[PDB]
Image 1 (cartoon, helix red, strand yellow):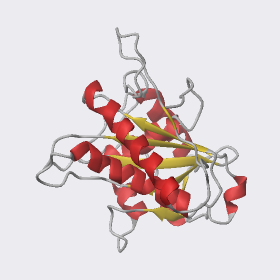
Image 2 (cartoon, rainbow, N blue to C red):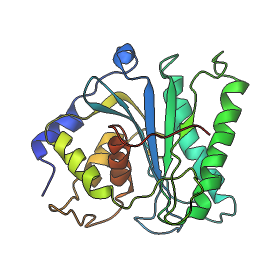
Image 3 (tube, one colour):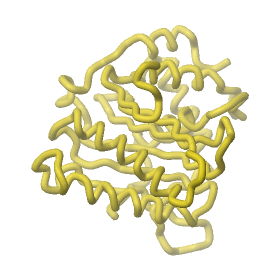
Image 4 (cartoon, rainbow, N blue to C red):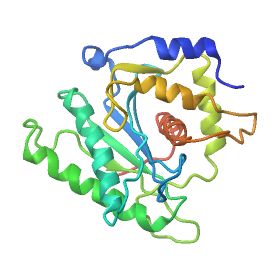
Length: 244
């Protein structure tokens, strides 16, 4: 009973443009992912959310509820074609617009996969722009979120979701029923059908939030929602993420 329907008419309604108003953006680009490694489950998709900043508010570029296909031996790489296949589409319609992006991968499933997952992300990102697109000779310049496991001093490029979920939700609903965030007119999708609305598909899933401690997800398929909210909590300030 959380996100107001007055905001939902607004957040569904207004379609601002980042093709023209790009110069009024922060040149950085947070992006989150939520890998779920099982298949054939209505909440086991993998979320994509990529967000930028205006002066004080936040703005959405692409959402992919990435299911797992059947018969997967190369499954982390497929997730890597998802998220990089998104970032290339954002950077594509935004020529010379962004300085550097920051990919976030959660490791609540395991710390083991996300290392080679983000490594395989930097692999294909490091592949693509040198092939074609434009002459951005290391233009959009990737960095990652490098975290520390509890009890291990070695920094790996991942993100724990331990203490952060409640201030992230409180930040998101702090902004969202105030009409802070918005979704771009040129919001990008690959997995969701170009016929159907992406923003409608988000807003259905946004409508399953819960109380002051927020034990959420009544339901199914929170991954887009949880993805957007961790993405926007990193769209504000926190500890520094860095280069790989």
